[PDB]
Structure formats: structure tokens, C-alpha cells
Amino acid sequence: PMAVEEVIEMQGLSLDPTSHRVMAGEEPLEMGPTEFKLLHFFMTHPERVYSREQLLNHVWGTNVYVEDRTVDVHIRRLRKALEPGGHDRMVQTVRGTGYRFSTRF
Image 1: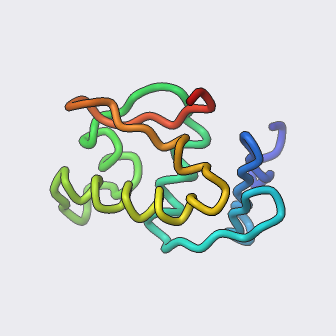
Image 2 (image 1 turned 90 degrees about the vertical axis):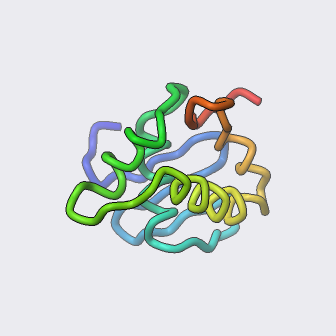
Image 3 (image 1 turned 30 degrees about the horizontal axis):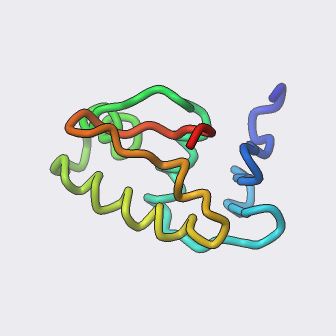
């Protein structure tokens, strides 16, 4: 995608950095700012697995302080927001290791 604020798309799921609009095809999806940031990170760092520690650093930063399970909490809310189109299946748990976003499922 040779464009910075360009719309990211994967398996029918699109995310607009400018308007913060996320869609399963043409149906709009609802999620908070943390989930959006998490989804944005996943769609741009696909297939690879990340520990909660890595996801905390990439998404929450450092000037805040959050526990690892908080990641699990927002992973849940994100999956929940992605259900309409079944895209929640793209947010996958890597047993006792972390999470990955995949087109394969």
C-alpha cells in the first residue's frame, strides 16, 4: 500500500486510518479506540505471533502501565466487534504464547 493513511484491507475487512471506519465488506463495525489500535497493529503485522508484552509495548506504550491479561480483555472486545462478518476468526490465540492475526483459519 504505497500511501501512509491509505485504507488497509484483508479478507473483506477494511480499516480507514483517517476516518477510523472499520468494515466487513460494506457493513460498519463498532469498537472502542483501544480495539481499533489493536486491530490496526494486527492488520499491519499479520501472521506473526506477538506476546502480550510486545502487544502492550506496540499498542499501549509505556507511559501508562497495564497488566498482561488486559490484553486478553481487549482481544475479547475486538473479537466481539468483528463477529458480524466472522472476521473474529482472524484474531487467533497462540496457546500460552500470545496472539497473531491471520487470513488462515
